[PDB]
Length: 65
Image (cartoon, rainbow, N blue to C red; front, side):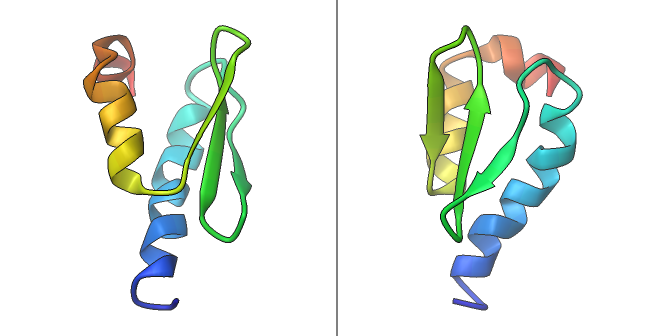
């Protein structure tokens, strides 16, 4: 976990401070799952890629985050 799994929650660390720069309260879920609050509908990602993709398809955050 240290080498692979930690990088997963490690990423959740950098965005944990950034999400606070928005109106979506960030929270680290399962040892490496990160949930965010947007448009009310809650979404979660267990891989830093899936998250980056979530924004890759929603530039609005990319520019702000």
